[PDB]
Length: 51
Length: 51
Image 1 (cartoon, helix red, strand yellow):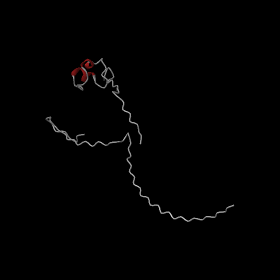
Image 2 (image 1 turned 135 degrees about the horizontal axis):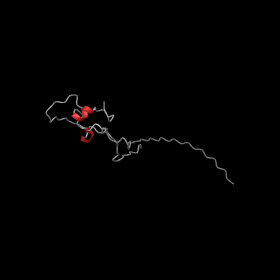
Image 3 (image 1 turned 90 degrees about the horizontal axis):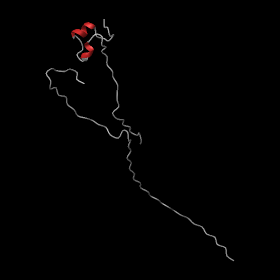
Image 4 (image 1 turned 90 degrees about the vertical axis):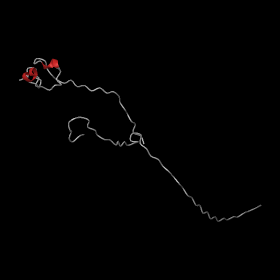
């Protein structure tokens, strides 16, 4: 139902009946459409707990 | 040759008046923010249960 196993059917992919955020190169059925989410920590604030 | 005997009584009324003053603090939790805010909708649709 999806050739790439990603949660968008080949029909949904080629016809564009899809989440629009899916980047255009992944509209093709043989190209998997998946998020890659990494967190980066811009800075770290320690506060000393002292009475 | 001498021999001396002595004997003493003492009353002592001591009145004391103390004042004291303390400021405690915690360096992690030293202040509390309370932000007054207001929402605006400059768009075209209404939005419900805004958070």
